[PDB]
Length: 13
Length: 232
Ligand SMILES: *[C@@H]1O[C@H](CO)[C@@H](O)[C@H](O)[C@H]1NC(C)=O
Image (cartoon, rainbow over the protein chains, first blue to last red):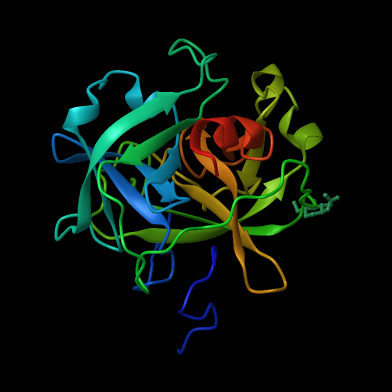
C-alpha cells in the first residue's frame, strides 16, 4: 500500500 | 503554509522535515522506506549529506523517528541561479517502519492529468506569513491548481513559468506555501481514497498575495527522473 491515511478528511466539529 | 491550519496527527504521514544541523530548512515526502522527494534549492548552500537529518509526524521539536541522510541527489540541470529543475531525492541511512503516523505516498504515472480547477492540499512547517518563522507544528491548506495560461499572464508570473512547473493557490491569495515549505508535498486523493504526489513546493513572490500563487515542481514531468534515481 501507498497513499493511505488512517485519519478521515471529514473531521468532528 | 500561509494562513495554515494545524494538521491532525496521522493526517499527512508522508510529510517529513529536513534539518541541517538540527534546524528546519525544508519539507520532503516519503516514497519508500528509504527514499524521500524534495527540492534541489534546499541544498543550495548546505551541501554536506552528513549534517542533514529527517524526521516525521506533526512535530519537529519533539522529533519522530529522526533519521540520518545517507545521501541526496539533485537534478543534473538544476543551477542555483535559476528556478528550473527544482527537484531532488534523499535516501536515509536506516529504513523506517510504517506506522499510522508514517507511511509512503503514491507517485502518479508519468502521464496522469489533473483538471485545472482541482482541489489539492499543501502542508509544511514553514512560515505563516512572508518573513515569518517556521512552526514546530505541521500545517495544511486547501488550494486549487491554476491554468498555465492564467499563470503566464505578465501581471502574474509570465515567462518565469517553465516546463515542469505549475501553479496552485488562489488568485485572491490568502492560502499559499511560504518559506520553510519547499520540497514538501502538494497532494490529491483519487476516488479510491488514495493520495498522490502532484507537486513539490518550489517558489513564489511573497506568500498569499493577489495574483501571486505558489509555483510547484510538476512530479509527472520528473516522474522518469525519480524512477532512474530511486527505482520507485
Ligand atoms: C475555476 O475557478 C476560477 C476561480 O478564480 C474561475 O475564474 C474559473 O472560470 C473556473 N474555471 C476555469 C478554469 O475556467
